Each structure stands twice: as structure tokens, then as C-alpha cells.
Amino acid sequence: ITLKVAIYPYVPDPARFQAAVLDQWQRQEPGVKLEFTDWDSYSADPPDDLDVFVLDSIFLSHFVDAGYLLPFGSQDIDQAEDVLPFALQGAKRNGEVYGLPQILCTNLLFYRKGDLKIGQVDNIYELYKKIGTSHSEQIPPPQNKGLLINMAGGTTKASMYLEALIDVTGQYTEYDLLPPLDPLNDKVIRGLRLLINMAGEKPSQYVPEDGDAYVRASWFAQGSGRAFIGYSESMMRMGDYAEQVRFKPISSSAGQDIPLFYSDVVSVNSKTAHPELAKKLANVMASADTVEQALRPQADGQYPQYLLPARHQVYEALMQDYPIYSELAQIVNKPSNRVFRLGPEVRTWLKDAKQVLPEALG
Ligand SMILES: *c1nc(C)nc(N)c1C
């Protein structure tokens, strides 16, 4: 018996995840072989021979209604009480749990220590009041000037549009029915344009030819820009500098915010020939032990990945050695937090949004 598995591809160090999963799997099932494969939910559906895999929850509704996944009954979920409540709830559809939460993500406002004025900023308009508009298109921005932020790519901008709308309306929704692309929401568009105005056009739309997703974090640590909005994982790349930066959650408006989080969940193929064994592996990949092992440094010169876990036990175990995880645990335990979900017609809607958003954003 060989199981085909795919870990989440977009992390600072996927090799650390692959080694943690293999190590933990072998402790319970040394005879069942694992064949690790490359798979991305943003540009592909689940292959028929891919047994276990990790996906971004915006695609969960589509996969469920298409008959691709195998639901997890209550007796198929290990230590459900340790999993953050909002994360567990965001993994349900048609009354069933369709995925096991592994990683969570959210943009944060990074500023340098000593710069107390930015420490008080709570939303993008207050940020604009402090740093103002960019006055250069150079890449990267001048030393200690402007905002660093990745807004390159269609789905990123489409995602940002939909998260902002929920803040504008002040009511959470899983978007079972996606919104009209014609009468576009003005408040949301003005907000997205403010971010571009603060960061510069070319700098905000830049894509490195080597595909380094954490390049803006390296520019910030070197002295570029005054503020940087990016995921928590950006800190692994900062390395030694991670201790010198400060960070806090930032809203796209003055209101109720409703903190939204991207959630990467572990699911099982409805077509798998090994249902219980597959469910056993899904639990291992999402267990507190393998996630802690994947986030911790595994060789000399290595730094923590700084990814957000979905179980309480991981934050507790990483805290002593890495005090940064204490502030991340606090952000993640807010009562109002929610998982970012999109309707069953995501793919088509994304195609349509690509023909109208760039023009609206200038
Ligand atoms: C979290 N959030 C996003 C949007 N993308 C990645 N890769 C992660 C880990």
C-alpha cells in the first residue's frame, strides 16, 4: 500500500513539512509508503489518484458540491477540542466537516521599533495619514519611505476585493452566491486604490522572475520602506531582523472589521481506495506534533517558518523558545475571527473579475 499525498506548496520551507509528515507517519504506519506529489488548489482540481491533499478554503465549496471530497464524521477527527473553533466551523458544508485545519493566514502591519507613530495605526486611512502617497516608482521604495505590499496578480486582487466587501457590509458571508461584477462597490474600490497610492504602482504589481514570494520582507529588513503589509510568514525571511520589527492587525476601514483568515485544510479524495488509512494520514498531517516540527528550525542557520497553526497546543509549545508566537497566539484567538470562504462558482467568477478589476483600479 502506497498513498499519494500533497502538502501545501506555498510556505517558506515545504521540505520541512514533507520531512515532518514522513517522520510522524512512520511512527504509526512504517509499512505504508508515501509518495509526495506537487499539487496546487489555485490552478487545478483534485486528481483521481491523489489520496490526501491540502487546499486553500476559498475552493472548499466548489470541491464539496462537485463530489470530490470524503466527509469526516465526528469519530474520524482526532482531538477536535484543541482546534480553534472558528477554524473547525469554517471547514463545514451541508452539515459535515470536509477538511482538517492545518495553517491559517492574515496580512499584518509591520513597522520598525522606535517608530511609535505607526504603532497606533488601526486601519488603512490612518496609515495614509501617516505615510502619505508614494512619490517614486523605483523598485524597491527608497530607504524608510512608503508602503511595501504585494498586490500583484488577479486572484489576489479579487480576494482582497471580496474580503473588503464583508467589512463594508459588516455581515459575514460564505458567498454561496457571489456578488455582481457590474455595479462594483465604490467604498471597496477606493480602499484598494489607497493601498496602491501608498505603495506605488510598479512596486505593488512587481513579480520577481524567480518567483520569490517573500522578497518584500527582505527589502524591509534591509531598510526599504517605512511600513510593510504582509503575512506572518514574512518573518522567516527577515531572519535575525524578525526580533527588531513590530506588527499588529490592520483593518481596511473604520467599523466592525470582522477578522478574516485564509485556511489551508487537509482533505481526502472521495475516490480513494483506502478511506480509513487516508483519514488516519489526514489527521497526522494536521496533528499538533507534525505542525510544530514543520515550523521549528531543522538545521543550522535556519529560522522558524512563522506560519499560523490552527491548534492551541502548537502555540503553547513554540512560545518559550520563540516569543513572537505569543503575540500571534493572541491575534488568532480573537472571538470575532472568521474563515474566508467563497462560493461553488469561484473559478468562473475569478475569470470574470480579471476583466474588470484592473481597469477599475487604474
Ligand atoms: C496563506 N495565505 C495565502 C493567501 N497564501 C499562502 N500561501 C498562505 C500560507
Image: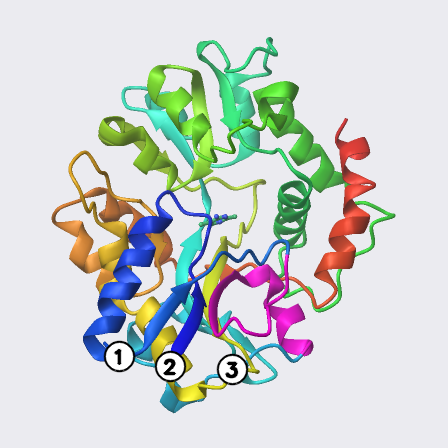
**Residue placed farthest to the right in the image?**
182
Asked whether residue 288 appears in the rendered view, the answer is yes
Measured as percent of width and height from the top left, residue 8 is found at 44, 56
The tag earlier along the polypeptide, 1 or 2, is 2
Q: Residue at x 31, y 48 (%)?
A: 328
Quick one: label 2, few (<14), some, or many (20+) residues within 10 Å? few
- Residue 283: percent from left, percent from top: 34, 75
* Residue under label 2: 1
Magenta-span inclusion, residue 65: yes
Kindly identify the amino acid type of the residue bearing the numbered disc 1: Gly
- Give how far across and how far down residue 187 sits, in percent: 72, 40
Which residues lie in the magenta part?
44-66
Question: Which amino acid is tagged 3?
Answer: Thr
Q: Secondary structure at mark 3?
A: loop
Q: Residue at x 34, y 59 (%)?
A: 333
Whether residue 309 is situated above or below residue 152 in the rendered picture? below
For the residues bearing labels 1 and 2, Cβ distance under 8 angstroms: yes
- For label 1, the SS is loop
Quick one: label 3 or label 2, which is nearer the N terminus?
Answer: 2
Residue for badge 1: 31
User: Is the C-beta separation of discs 3 and 2 under 8 Å?
Assistant: no
Instruction: Classify 4 as above or below 96.
Output: above
Separation of disc 3 and disc 1 at Cα?
A: 18 Å
Whether 218 is among the magenta residues is no
Q: In terms of image quadrants, where is residue 179?
A: bottom right
Of tags 3 and 1, the one toward the viewer is 1
Q: Secondary structure at mark 2?
A: loop
Front position among marks 3 and 2: 2
Q: Which residue is mark 3?
A: 272
